[PDB]
Image 1 (cartoon, rainbow, N blue to C red):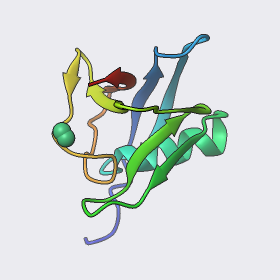
Image 2 (tube, helix red, strand yellow):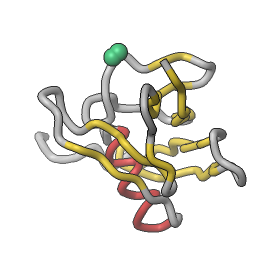
Image 3 (cartoon, protein in one colour):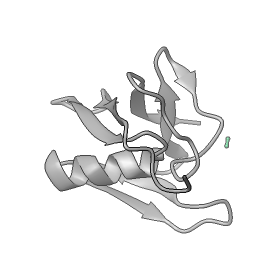
Image 4 (spheres, helix red, strand yellow):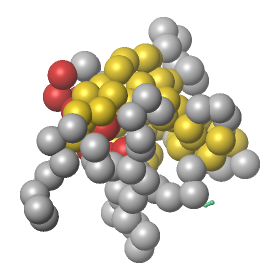
Amino acid sequence: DHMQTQEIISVTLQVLSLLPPYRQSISVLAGSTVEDVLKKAHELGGFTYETQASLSGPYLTSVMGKAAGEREFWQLLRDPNTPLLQGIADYRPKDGETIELRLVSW
Ligand SMILES: [C-]#N
């Protein structure tokens, strides 16, 4: 029906731009967004982050207490080393995917 998936998937959320690195397998409903994964990692796995409103949805500004500085941003990637084409509130990871948040300068 127009109800929710029921099948639970596992998405690995990893942050290698920090010491110690963050890596946790997160269980969400199939169809959850990256933002949903962050929320669940926050609820259960001591993950913190900040966003701010944008014209194209929430923009990720800080991860695990580390804010992006000048000419820097938290890049969203799926394994292997592949930037996402959508932001956190749009991309819906598949079962077994690894989502990486990487602090990069431009
Ligand atoms: C935006 N790239």
